[PDB]
Image: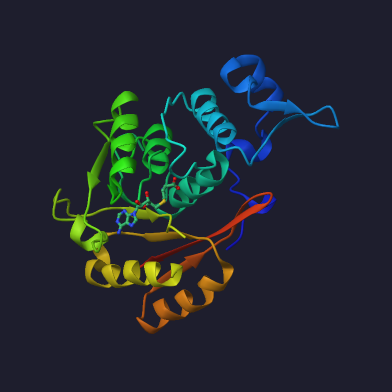
Length: 254
Ligand SMILES: Nc1ncnc2c1ncn2[C@@H]1O[C@H](CSCC[C@H](N)C(=O)O)[C@@H](O)[C@H]1O
């Protein structure tokens, strides 16, 4: 499948994208990173990671009420793009209500802990955040605690060679609804490790998903899943102008 306006229909920033002028007038700690371009427009220098951090932290504060602390030394996520994936998963696990508790896994949560944070806020989803990087693990366990989401999000430091399988030994939950992953920059080799772990977990997770960075990666993975005889295999492409990612998910369910 593929979504109109190249991004998910339920995305906040599809109809109402970020307004630099507005955010500068509200958050004077963001006003410092914004500069007036030639066209008179209020613009952020996307090269400066401190500027980009200021935007991402402000959009979380402004639109989700999330106050996060993230280091420059680590990846700065781009709020609207990550949000498409949150909505795609919503669609996959057939969102719809108050007594229907849905639980997922985030393979590589990052310093931000962006997916579990959005996910637990927007929908109240229980998450199992995994991390190999200590710095990332420290900041994520911190952002979760400071937004009092300690109850829904369970951040866990994990060994290097370990993925999905190994992580589901603490805690012991029978059925997980989804698992999202944003592979770090071979890419194909990573999702292949996810595919394999999914072959042994099968119906224990309703949906296994992966946000890809390269379109070339879709063709072999689509073929791998097909060779392994995976019943449902779904894919889409998201967008944020210059940026473009390819989310792919697969289920063993009829
Ligand atoms: N085998 C593995 N298991 C768990 N986490 C891993 C891992 N390999 C890498 N990671 C971690 O996963 C992260 C990938 S970056 C994805 C971060 C986040 N979801 C975002 O979009 O902001 C890194 O912080 C890295 O330390």
